[PDB]
Length: 295
Length: 295
Ligand SMILES: [Co+2]
Ligand SMILES: [Co+2]
Ligand SMILES: [Co+2]
Ligand SMILES: [Co+2]
Image: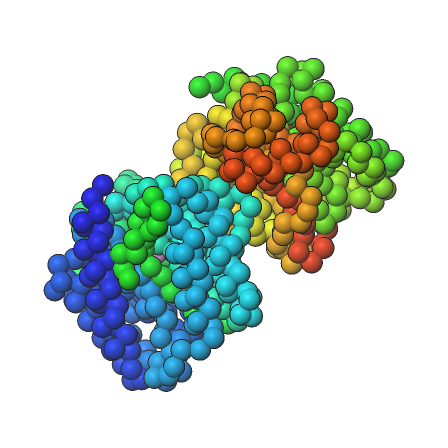
């Protein structure tokens, strides 16, 4: 409803993402990197739209450190930094892949070019299948495979994944027409593996879905807290770690997940352990072009 | 508006579908089969929602005979019969695979069970991803591959493919939640091939997409007929082969395509030419269950 906040969120997302790239040096602790970016988001005037994802190599997405994580970056690691910022619910979602301490390679170039190719065809009145075809052709002509179950997505106020997605493959019936004012995150994922991700432990990210009558008090009040503190945007297990002892925390989240009150987003790994590269920008559809808010 | 028109469309689609199975015998002309099915739809009181698709073996979908087509069913052929009926815009979309002159096999069973699995979990409140998972699990545990770029779809009045899809694979962000009153066609495709379909000539089905000024007169009268008789639902090239000679028809159709008035839907073939099996039903989502309009 207001492009000013979408542009502000995008400007902030761009700034933090570019600083995150500078911090991604061999030896950097992931936890330290994550907290710096999220603090930087704060210091600039926005709130995180979701916890910063730092996904290494075959880990495609949904990895955000936790208090006690000793993972450090290593030279040669294909680190995907996925950052989201929101200004009053208006979101900017962007991502880049850095090969730690090294230079970009062909796998990375395929994902980045696929993104450029989809932005180039996007405008009001274009069918989503057109973006999908653009993305897939760029990835496949370079000898890589697109990830079929991870895609771009429509973004609405306080709703990161609005329902309509922009696949990284051409689907003949993806006939949703981009409308003026539509906000979408386009995110090609390329890999040398099979082209599919699966969920694996641990679950570091969750999202509130519904108020469920939970009996045990500890879980009942956590839902209430999650509810008004995070609302409908994804939150990290890390964000709740100092609020209560880890043991009961894990139990409460489980109880809430088992009752269907919140849903967990387990780490996503490429099925054949193939390295995954990803690039992403958020766009606002205009009549004849698109505005890339995170560029 | 009314679940009654939806129920009515489904009853006719089922009857017609059950008749088509009986006629799928060796030596049957696809053209004879398509014409009989479509005439029966009209005899029963409905109008085709799309032309009867008769897709054999590696041809996954979008094949509908044309006048002069000599294709006949051979014993052993995996015939996918996809039929749709509408009653004043309210659609029933259903499909079955028959191994011509033979009994059902594991490939067909996987697709069928995948469908039954998705339906058993569907009800208001469930995210689309849960249906994707159910489908993918039944196809994969039997050793086959779900088709990644062909899938189920939300159905709206006079809109066969409404935007929201139900994939045959699990995607973690398919979080559209089924709502009471939603109408969807669940359609698992399974194959022994790679699991992906590509577009190949000919284009035997088209669909009116936008009201554009046509400079040519026969193209303009043609578009007038399309808008008048088919509206926004797909139509077969076959349905127009009598209005004007082939050459005039081809050129008028190309002018309309270039003008952006209609969109062509080429035949879909499994990329590694693997046999494709498909089953499909239309469902109306209820509070605690679903009505399968096409059973
Ligand atoms: Co992102
Ligand atoms: Co995204
Ligand atoms: Co169908
Ligand atoms: Co269908």
